[PDB]
Image (cartoon, rainbow over all chains, first blue to last red; front, side, top):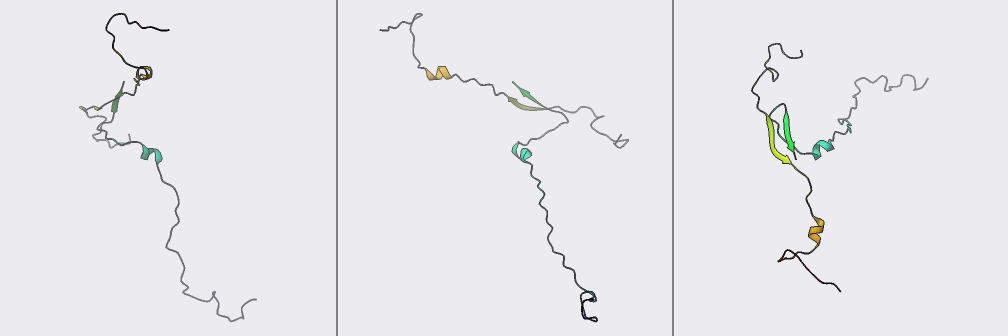
Length: 53
Length: 53
């Protein structure tokens, strides 16, 4: 009903390139405060032992 | 049974050395406020005497 009958419109065009941006939006947090706060150490066995007084 | 059938794992081996750290954690307090606050002096006898008025 629209377009002057035999009008060259976006429907008839072939080879229209798509537009996909090269950015992926990810904002999920992955911080580990407790693990960052505490210290590091080495274990040499399945069971790890220490002492208190 | 989620292990290879003929697999040498920590379950069946023997002679594993223990893992005992070389630190002893003691946090008991031993401060003496009243001793630090008051003065110090020398007594030269069994009985110490002074005067008031």
